[PDB]
Image (cartoon, each protein chain N blue to C red):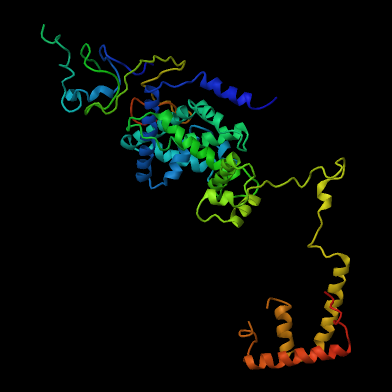
Length: 345
Length: 98
């Protein structure tokens, strides 16, 4: 039964049950997030294990077993053996070093209780950026992709509040997704900030003139390197692919697509020309001294058409030689037996 | 399990305000730290501090509440060794096999 509410609800359910203290607890978790990486960074030292390892293995010990490591990203690492093994070394580390394992673990745990206490902090924000071209959910989803990305970076020591800090990164993440997923034909961020201007300028001109601006009014208005061919060209692209499937004519049954022809496929009269062309050129291929014919033959023919590095051994002057001569003899033995004359093309 | 404290004393509490008064982190004055009952392990004066922070000066402030949260779970402290199945629990300090 209709999504949206469930999530909006599921959030408030653990949000409405797990809100965070405006300072304290947030500052608490924070210290436990930073002392986390810092910790792990030392584990890697005392263990010659890549940070990427510790970070993962510590996460599973908390988030999920060997289950979440299998289906997500294939068995590169031993769901069973490899993971416990690593942990074995961590727990085997003397008090002085194991200290950090517990801190690491206690570290990632805090991250957990800092990302949730704001899932609504995202929703609110998302509430604004909406009708651009993404479900409310996605808009919220891409907002959370930003919430976390904002935790990895917050420095609690620099007294300024978290909530805020999150705002920035969140909007950052939503926009990207917007610019990057919004359409069917990928357009760059560049030619995006630029289309909006044009959409806008289109209105400023709608404002006073009355005549829907010619690609001149718009061009002058926009800026420098803006011609008339430019704006006209900018829009066809700023368009929206029309559904290959849409009611046409006295719309009833007749579906659009059936009005669009084909081209790759040669229609019977052409499939018959390659027939005649092939054989006839191939019959007029034999009445030749293969020593040079078969070089231009396959040249345009087989691979691709460069006269220089053309022939195997012999130099150039013998290329054109038999070329220009064979070609011509080839041209007049056909003038007689008129086969290609009436251009098969 | 009570959390962030304020200021009334400091009996058997956390390692946070162990710096606010070096006495018990370089020397050993906590034993004489009591205001006056020494003539006629955590503790502290009537009230000489705020909340949680790094006190080189106030570079880690957090003036607030004291959430006393109850977690329905069992609290062990001095577990030992019963080697029938793989080592479970911990020791008084040594191998915290967990």
